[PDB]
Length: 171
Ligand SMILES: Nc1ncnc2c1ncn2[C@@H]1O[C@H](COP(=O)(O)OP(=O)(O)OC[C@H]2O[C@@H](O)[C@H](O)[C@@H]2O)[C@@H](O)[C@H]1OP(=O)(O)O
Ligand SMILES: [Mg+2]
Image (cartoon, rainbow, N blue to C red; front, side):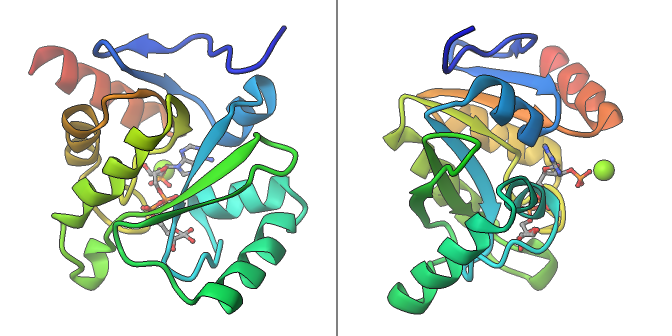
């Protein structure tokens, strides 16, 4: 036992790894330097990954997020900010993917993944792929084509994990 030690990930490419896991359980076990949040521009951590991370910090992430946004104003779609990882990680990189359910520009998903290249190693979810309504296969593709640093993707759903791995390791 040490820190940033990932286990049970499938190596997709030289720098992209994928596991069927809860990003919160992975954060707790690994204590990564950086865990990524699938955030909105307001850092209102209502559901999905954001709700699960915030709940595991006993709401400390939401209190910090409320203070940050009241001070700085909202993020841009495709942007990020580095805040505390609380009890889960050294840092949390809050990254805003486009909300395609509200017609936001899918091109901003590439801008969102570009934020990952500022960090050597990240534990991350598939951006925009849940509540934000992007195709998860497309989100994995943009991740693989954009991110050059080491990214460990945690995919909660068993069936989604199997679909992502089979489509990737065919195409
Ligand atoms: N605990 C978890 N660990 C790992 N992955 C997780 C976990 N919970 C959900 N996911 C997955 O992450 C992906 C991203 O889903 P969301 O967390 O909904 O992020 P997205 O970028 O789609 O939506 C962001 C919005 O979701 C709101 O919660 C947040 O405050 C913001 O407004 C989906 O494939 C989502 O899968 P699903 O569609 O919820 O089954
Ligand atoms: Mg699901």
